[PDB]
Length: 478
Ligand code: NI
Ligand SMILES: [Zn+2]
Ligand SMILES: [Zn+2]
Image 1 (tube, rainbow, N blue to C red):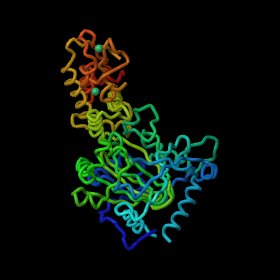
Image 2: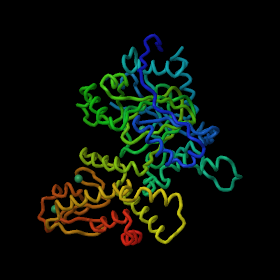
Image 3: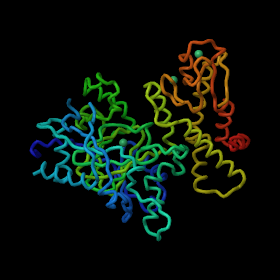
Image 4: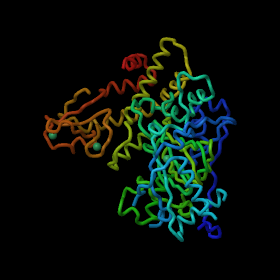
């Protein structure tokens, strides 16, 4: 079934590859921050851990490897570009799935990475026959278990414990100090608690971008390589347009195709249309880093098991803001509360400044928070921007609206953590301040607004980030 004479490998330049020291790996967020200047213009990058950094994998224990079940879905590789969703497949264990991957490869190819790539794109672009494969995607590490070790009390000291404490352990990455996801109490699947992906030959994750345009970190625990293609964030729009222009219209039946994640488009076609694409080959024991609003896709070269999680350093905030605004225009539901995270970061920073006031010990965390909140600080800019948005929206209404001190918009599903407009007629139903008028049609006397913080309190927060001790004192008490 393999036809190497008609291979269709695209000519894609390689994404950058990094080799961090041990010291570099002692501080994940700082290293990511430094990687930004070098690799954000690419969209993705490959990260090779220092020599001998390789955590044990609990999934390999036979109680899980042989007996733990996960569902799969069916992908028709020949239909990914030229033609809908991935149908239910059979249940698998890791052992069974590895076995079937072996069977499949031997039948199919009677093979190095580039051969596999050429054949994959041959199937996608110009299919001679139908090719179906199974994919175990978005598996929740809570039920099944994580690929990373966890600390277990009552055991002798081992390297496993050290790995379980590590910041590059994807179970710990999301809520590290410096990542605003730490201010979300719920263990959101995928976003804060890592997802597991079990792949076989040709298993595909189509073109997509992360929810809220977050950072994405992926670790390949075991198995065959995974081929990645990535688009720079600043070209996202371009990509989108090309998708509308090179598959016209697989955007008719479903204006919402981009977010369905069932469509593949060759990097060849993207390059002919002027969209820069970069390539990475992820092998077991390696990381793939994905930047805000950076489209990515790819496929597996055989049986493997990967883990993925989100992270949100302060420099993401801007993007994040944009994202939810976009969602509001798209009438799409959010996966998290942005204002909650922003406010959380602001209050944490304010607390650190307040601690500096009392001449308490200066810690690396306190330092990091301080360097992002002055007049020029990124956090301060984010908060100030948000507050300005609130002021403008508030000004547009409250003609008799009335206010009450303290949830999605009924119309655009905007998260209402900060403020929510409602009426007497319809309690338990809310609108964002943009669509406050669209809620009811009642007279102003019956309208009103739930508000978490008065406007002067918010401006006080902005001032506190800029270093006013009275404002700092005020917000430290919250
Ligand atoms: Ni992703
Ligand atoms: Zn709204
Ligand atoms: Zn009303």
